[PDB]
């Protein structure tokens, strides 16, 4: 079987939530996740006298510091009969040999394993910061609930009383609503990412059109972070100070494709927020034997004999997508 | 007798269906097409505790998986009488040379042959995502039937009861009808490609021309399809969570021009829906000698003798356009 | 006499009816032009069994293929007594040399000469796409009629019914009228070339200026081919999906300048339309002696003896501006 | 132990006050900070004939001198239990090395320390420019007062009969009121930076948005100096000759965040105003031996033995932010 060196992917296509807020990652060397080891936030400086004295600063973890990671180990078979996809610049002549066919099917399995894991991680991040709460479910797995600690003031519901869909489309100005909803953000917002359906009603107002910018974007390197995600991510322009992004990602359930976000919703927040990317241990004999207990991903290839005399491929991981301060965003439930 | 390396075209101008739905291709190393050998889609990551053996993600195929490809091989004359278009100041001295003239005419003949094969692929694709059924028939070809698996709920006919035409053009709103039609789609819908006359009445609604956002800089990179296909595809604008595309493409029969789509239809579709581009084997005596049995296209230039003492150039293929999920679309038949 | 190879112009400034619709050129090797030799259309395909052989594919579609090229050979005399545009600080005393000045006047004569061919070619193009019928009639030239094949339904006049002049200039939307004239075009339209006096009334409608996205640098890339001929061509901008451009080129008669298009005229065409730039044969003994029977232009410098004792320079060309599909464009006579 | 030269930080994150008003710095070689030692201002010339010598010029600067700065000195331990951040594309082999892990911990502790000092260095600046009065407190410090020498008229709070909150929101123009506030500013006003809670009140006026040209690009230098703080500061636009900034940075208490400015307040000044950055002696036994008595910061690492047996890293400085003309800024307490 192919060794552990079969890890040649080096593709960074994290979709808009692991790249914009959850950039930093903290893999752990224990079964669970403890927030005590996390550096946390810096304190004040606390004026003291001259050399007379001096007191030591300890960065605590607060109240809750024990979470259970979402361990995952999806498996594929490497049956050497699947018809290989016609990737470009592929000569069938140096392809008929099994030594290359198997070597490429292994890489294909690695690619779609990594894609599934990363997409589940993004689903986890969206479930985390769309409402602040979160849960872990699954067949043959004990349910687990994770609570960030989102304040109730950051879950503004537009349906109650005053919506946006029942106002004049040529006289109503939605800037005041945006300011009133972003006032309680605990920090200046610059990202107001919408939904594909939710953006239509917002843009339908005429007052936004003239003020809205389309000048290619002049915010930051964010346009570079968007151009790679050309399919499900669109960058629109300037609201005057903040950037507008419409994101329409999809994920594949049992047989049906669904969006990450609830249909008519939007979020305000900051592009400089702190998003934890904690990971548990890869509870495998080989990983512990090779000192790779603290890692984000773990590929493995082997051949099982006797009853299932087949060769398999696994990518084990354990995400616990976490947010430092849940109250730095506002989740508007539009209607 | 030119060599077998005469396939230098590099013209990826597939017309709006081989590029939005059937982006994934699969050559086969066997005569028929065994759909069970397709790797298939990917489910999320379904969680398991790291003490129990994981479940193998296997490509569960359908009840029927043994299809027959539609072998197609057009051949052309290379008689050095056909006039040649003038490339910009391409040294007209060498034109009189027959050796260069035949080599030049081979290239144009190959472009014509390839264009003569692009259309059968989309004659298959239009039937596939318009009805879920397709018959391959022709002179000296035994009829073949392909049942994609489309159900009744994805073949709504507007004539069944209340129709759009027999309403009031200035007051009626079709958004509710569009939502009802998209309800039974088994997945997100964002593309509703129309007909050149199936759209002239939908726009006639007073509410539609107000709701439709015809502004440039629209949803996504889909406008690239407009730039590539400036001859048959237009992009009318936005409609909320769905774009408006008018496809007046035409295919030419023996002497006449005809439309791909019937006059009054629309397709509630997903731009991310996967479509198979499976191909059969090149069932040619020469092809097996060089190991080109599993390939998409196969050119061959040769010289016939005895009765038709001329020389021909032929291109063989076997397109079997397929969809993994036929129920991902809705074919509404307007009236 | 100067050598024939002294033909250095390479400054093609074709005015938007030879660079937008008539890109492809077909020089001929026969005194007349045989349209049947043009490639034209290619049939779709035939579903054939892999065993039996298919039928040969021919080049059909055209019936009448007889046309008379409009031979044009203007000449200039090259006496060295003219006044010349003094190059800024390049000719301190080189002008004193008669040979250098004569070579300069030869170059300038050719530069002025090519315009007398470009103007007639563009006039041919306007005659083609404004009515579909063209007449060749001049002194010492027999009158000949050429008909593109344009149907009568594409020469619709705004006078019939309610013209735009007798209409509201504040509330009415001409988009309905524009599209009502656009179905009978056989292909999506995106070019609406106007005449400034005809375009003046269309600009008046408030719905236009509300919809006329005059934002420069739009997704349309035609302006790249427009700014080169900025003398008489503007670029008004986008109109949703279609592109509005104003053309006011004026061709010089014997001493007077006349507009290419009548005042209240407008066209609907596609920027990727196929236009033929077929050329006849230069029926000159000198060209035939060097095998230049098939070419676009053929300069000739030669000195006369005895009665008109001077030196002359001819340029001979046989332009036969043709259209593949004459019904693709629609020419409306505004009112 | 880490060498004293291990001071590789090169991060400049001054929060909009040390980066715009308090540029120049004056570290001191004496324990207390004597104000009478600043360079000061200069007389004009004192005209003198060129036969007689002129009096030598002497500039002193200020009278009240014997101030006393705070002597903040935060510490940190290097307990090698912290879960180190997974730096992108770093190998796991190096993480096993204890020396590299210790160096990484020291480097992170340096960042945490330096982010703890700038908080006081900015709280002092905010307190100085709101009232010109600022007291230093803290356990075991004997609170020390700082009277900048403000006038009384430069504290105009809107508390009369008419305030900005209880008047007309459509016809009132705040230009006159802003100019009346800026009249007693001892200079030309240039910055009207807001606290966002107080900003939202000003933003509601239509007379503001009818003239607030919030075009992207502040002045070509301000937005260059403020993009680094994408988390705390934001730029609104230009109000004519002046710009508007919204500062929302928060200073953290022992466990809780607090705002630098009172919510409904604004302050007016200039970007060219001079602000002193006087420091004091770094009263350290080793710093005296290394000839660094007068400096801005002083890192130190040591290993304690026996009772608090650990290894400590400490940063110590002495900030005594000052101004030359404290009465040039006007702090309006809105209502």
Image (cartoon, coloured by chain):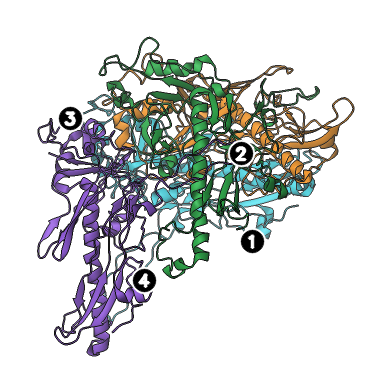
Chain colours: A orange, B green, C purple, D cyan
Q: Chain of mark 1?
A: D
Please identify the quadrant where the N terminus of chain C is shown: bottom left
Q: Are marks 1 and 2 in contact (CB under 8 Å)?
A: no
Q: Which mark is residue D291?
A: 1
Q: Is the residue at mark 4 from the same chain as the one at mark 1?
A: no
| Residue D195 visible in the current orientation | no
Q: CA distance from mark 4 to mark 1?
A: 92 Å
Q: Are marks 3 and 2 in contact (CB under 8 Å)?
A: no
- Circle 4 residues within 10 Å: few <14, some 14–19, many ≥20: many
- Circle 3 residues within 10 Å: few <14, some 14–19, many ≥20: some
Q: Nearer the viewer, residue B129 or A10?
A: B129
Residue on which the image places disc 3: C172
Residue D84 is left or right of residue B52, and the answer is left
Is the residue D152 above or below the residue B208 in the image? below
Residue D50 on image: x %, y %? 27, 80
Residue B271 is left or right of residue A42, and the answer is left
The label nearer to you, 3 versus 4, is 4
| Residue C65 visible in the current orientation | yes
Q: CA distance from mark 1 to mark 2?
A: 99 Å
Residue C294 on image: x %, y %? 36, 66
Residue D74 on image: x %, y %? 63, 42
Q: Which mark is residue C52?
A: 2
Q: Chain of mark 2?
A: C
Among numbered discs 2 and 4, the one appearing first in the sequence? 2
Is the residue D291 above or below the residue A236 in the image? below
The label nearer to you, 4 versus 1, is 4
């Amino acid at each position: 079987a192919q060794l552990l060196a079969a890890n040649e992917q080096k593709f960074k296509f994290d979709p808009l939530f692991l790249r914009l807020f959850f950039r930093e990652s903290y893999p752990f060397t224990t079964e669970k996740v403890y927030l005590s080891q996390i550096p946390g936030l810096v304190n004040m400086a606390l004026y003291v006298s001259p050399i007379v004295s001096g007191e030591v600063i300890r960065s605590r973890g607060g109240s809750t510091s024990e979470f259970t990671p979402g361990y995952v180990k999806p498996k594929h078979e490497v049956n050497p009969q699947m018809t290989l996809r016609r990737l470009p610049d592929e000569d069938p002549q140096n392809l008929a040999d099994p030594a290359y066919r198997r070597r490429r099917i292994i890489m294909q399995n690695m690619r779609d394993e990594e894609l599934a894991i990363a997409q589940v991680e993004e689903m986890q991040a969206v479930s985390a910061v769309l409402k602040g709460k979160y849960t872990m479910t699954g067949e043959a797995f004990d349910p687990v609930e994770v609570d960030m600690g989102r304040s109730e003031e950051n879950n503004i519901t537009q349906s109650g009383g005053t919506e946006w869909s029942k106002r004049d489309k040529s006289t109503y100005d939605p800037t005041d609503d945006i300011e009133a909803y972003a006032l309680n953000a605990s920090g200046v917002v610059n990202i107001i990412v919408f939904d594909p359906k939710g953006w239509a009603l917002f843009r339908s107002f005429k007052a936004v059109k003239e003020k809205l910018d389309t000048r290619r974007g002049s915010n930051s390197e964010l346009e570079t972070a968007v151009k790679d995600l050309g399919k499900a991510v669109s960058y629109k322009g300037m609201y005057g100070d903040v950037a507008i992004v419409v994101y329409s990602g999809q994920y594949v359930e049992n047989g049906v494709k669904k969006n990450f976000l609830p249909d008519n919703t939007m979020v305000l927040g900051n592009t400089q927020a702190r998003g934890l990317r904690t990971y548990g241990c890869i509870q495998d004999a080989d990983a512990q034997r090779e000192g790779i207990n603290a890692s984000a991903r773990y590929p493995k290839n082997w051949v099982t004999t006797g009853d299932p005399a087949r060769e398999f491929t696994m990518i084990q991981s354990a995400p616990l997508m976490l947010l430092a301060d849940p109250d730095e965003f506002v989740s508007v439930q539009l209607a």
